[PDB]
């Protein structure tokens, strides 16, 4: 089934076009995922010049099919069940005391490659805020991503809050409301309530002159213990 497309290392391509407060930008990413280990590594380039928002604000937007679901809970993996035809992933991301991003993405195979194509619009960012002020540290926290079935849409609803460290030691929150729906017309696995536990490290390629982000990320599904 879909899960079987993820037993090995799979190439990943990400393409994003964005507008935040009228600042236009594009990002292209390349790397690889190994869902067997819940692992991905990606390098993202801002192909339009300087990225006009902090890189950490784009991490969640820029392939949850690479999560590792433990044996006991493999039936809860909607993301892989929708493959290869894929899924639409939509979000609104509300930065507390600040603006919001609205995103629409299609995640699917194109040949051997797992592709994430995204459009992002951001509005209502404050000139005195942390986002347009570039006050976010270049680091990334560990989160819980809550997933539930959305039987009316034959998909899932996802909700979580990310924590973005600010230079002064405050923490800027981003509330994510997400939904995913299959692209194909065939049945999917709909899960029961569960979560993904995430960890990410951000780095740079010291040789790269372009504005960019290297992401190493590990994600494991989990649920209330029994």
Image (cartoon, helix red, strand yellow):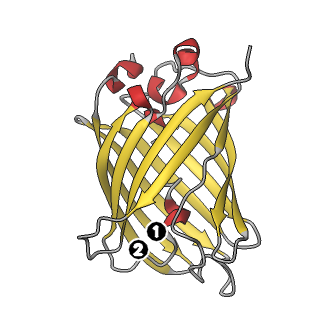
Label 1 SS: strand
Q: Disc 1 and disc 2: Cα gap in Å?
A: 5 Å
At 54% across and 31% down in the image, what residue appears? 220
Q: Nearer the viewer, residue 38 or 192?
A: 38
Q: Mark 1–mark 2 contact, CB under 8 Å?
A: yes
Residue 75's x, y, as percent?
A: 56, 15
The image quarter in which residue 203 lies: bottom left
* Quadrant placement of the N terminus: top left
Residue 94's x, y, as percent?
A: 69, 62
Whether residue 154 is visible: no
Position of residue 34 in the picture relative to residue 105 (left or right)? left
Q: Nearer the viewer, residue 56 or 52?
A: 56
Residue 218's x, y, as percent?
A: 48, 40
At 66% across and 41% down in the image, what residue appears? 144
The image quarter in which residue 181 lies: top right
Position of residue 43 in the picture relative to residue 87 (left or right)? left
**Vertical arrangement, residue 32 with respect to residue 141, above or below:** above
Mark 2: give few (<14), some (14-19) or many (20+) Cα within 10 Å.
some
* Quadrant placement of the C terminus: top right
Disc marking residue 70: none
Position of residue 217 in the picture relative to residue 100 (left or right)? left
Disc marking residue 25: 2
Mark 1: give few (<14), some (14-19) or many (20+) Cα within 10 Å.
many
Label whose residue precedes the other's in the sequence (1 or 2): 1
At 39% across and 42% down in the image, what residue appears? 40
Disc marking residue 18: 1
**Vertical arrangement, residue 186 with respect to residue 168, above or below:** above
């Amino acid at each position: 089934k879909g899960e079987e497309l993820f037993t090995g290392v799979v190439p990943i391509l990400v393409e994003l076009d964005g507008d935040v407060n009228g600042h236009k930008f594009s990002v292209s990413g390349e790397g690889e995922g190994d869902a067997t280990y819940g692992k991905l590594t990606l390098k993202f380039i801002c192909t339009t010049g300087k990225l006009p928002v902090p890189w950490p604000t784009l991490v969640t937007t820029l392939v949850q099919c690479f999560s590792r679901y433990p044996d006991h809970m493999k039936r809860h993996d909607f993301f892989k069940s929708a493959m290869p035809e894929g899924y639409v992933q939509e979000r609104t991301i509300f930065f507390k005391d600040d603006g919001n991003y609205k995103t629409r993405a299609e995640v699917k195979f194109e040949g051997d490659t797992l592709v994430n194509r995204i459009e992002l619009k951001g509005i209502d960012f404050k000139e005195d805020g942390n986002i347009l002020g570039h006050k976010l540290e270049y680091n990334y926290n560990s989160h819980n991503v809550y997933i539930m079935a959305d039987k009316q849409k034959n998909g899932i609803k996802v909700n979580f809050k990310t924590r973005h460290n600010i230079e002064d030691g405050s923490v800027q929150l981003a509330d994510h409301y997400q939904q995913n729906t299959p692209i194909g017309d065939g049945p999917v696995l709909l899960p029961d309530n569960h979560y993904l536990s995430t960890q990410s490290a951000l780095s740079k390629d010291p040789n790269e002159k372009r504005d960019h982000m290297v992401l190493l990320e590990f994600v494991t599904a989990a649920g209330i213990t029994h």
